Image (tube, rainbow, N blue to C red; front, top):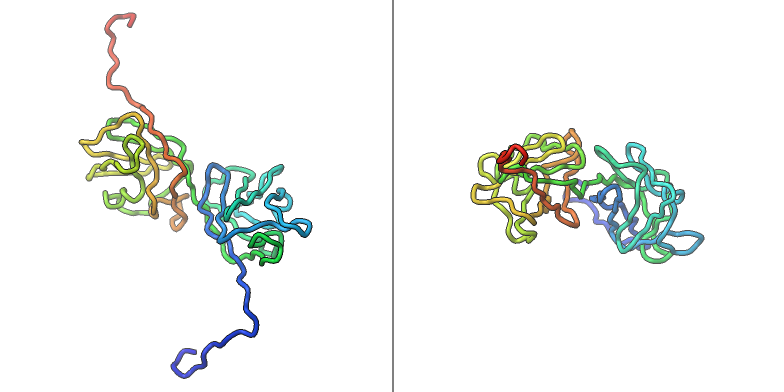
Length: 253
């Protein structure tokens, strides 16, 4: 009730079972998509428990926005509490995955046939988890290539902001991040992101760049309120992209 005088909720006659939902996707390792599950799971084929199913069976269970569908001649595989699959084409802009709207019974929790089955609930926006490449265009300017269009959604890109989006490691060790320029640390232009370091910091072979854990401001697509990026299983090497001087000592040299 909405007042003090109301009765309490009491014990159920029979213990109620929990229908599992679909966790946030938060994976794009290319086009290979990984969907994390709240627990261990297994498919139900021919009254038995098996980890591998085909595209025809797999398409019944899941649905995507923008008409993706799963790739033909491929096997959806579950290992641990994760689900691994491939799509018809690379996803550009937002995409969403969800459990079959008209119900389904092939995907069940536990590692046996007795356990419950999945249901629709709500969607799971897919977050990019990889970068294309990056290079040094100057001694303190480093430009990174996002796989898709992005947007920061009007956030002022002070140094307090940039440290949350992107970071530049030294010598491939995560304990020596490099200071940014307190003036204008970063900027965004479609697929290109600018990183400006401090005057004392300089580029050297072996550095690595990545998205800092907890990013929330950089997003996908043009519209705000979409999902941000996440960290990748391996950092992106930084390659040289500038030269100091080119001069003609001889006419043939």
